[PDB]
Length: 323
Ligand SMILES: [Zn+2]
Image (cartoon, rainbow, N blue to C red; front, side, top):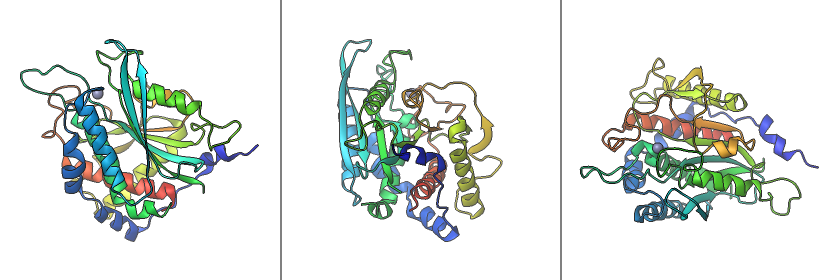
């Protein structure tokens, strides 16, 4: 009876030195991400809409052009909603599908439904078009390094459909894609042929990005079982800052502060957290002032803050994977 599902408890990062940190800082391009990964997602894309289809095609195409050996799966399912039965499609992109362990980055790609109001359309720029584009830019920026994985540990990206309530949040109207995928992963043996371990036991850590892109985000350390990984984010931010590798950034206004949040925030990590998966929840508190308004748009995004977080996240992922 293997103790492999316990490895995540002892897993340590392989920390990058200054030279490698400068390399990662220089290897990501906020302007390329903006043009190639972000702008095509700044469209209406509530579940089942033509925009959902276009967003999903864009996400798959951007991953498909990369050199690393990504395996794309579309997880399509039905769920009851306030509007009756509807179809939803999660996007899962995985390196080394049979690898026992994966570090998982995720966000939601649907946008909240709103009827057009005075000709304005809701595009959820921070919620969560930016997180989607950050995951795509990370895949692009680290592509040569990720190609090398082609420690039975690899990387997986999940873009959830249906995170948003069709009305106002309720237990039955929200988290459609995550409630479904968590249940499916919980009931899927992993690695293939296993007798008693599931894909959820294989999830070393779920790093869920949400509501990113506004100025001065502050991310609290929500959970004690991922606190040491939150501390690594703080360390990475501090070192990139001291190396002069962040833009318009100060330690007094740092993003990862020493501070917990005891309350519960409803998001896509919930169905995973309640099945025992460790979560690093990269959602700011308080939420962007533009949250769920037509002003959550491109104009209100803070370019250098997103650039800075791309660097921190990319360093975190390489250190976790020992790349
Ligand atoms: Zn939202």
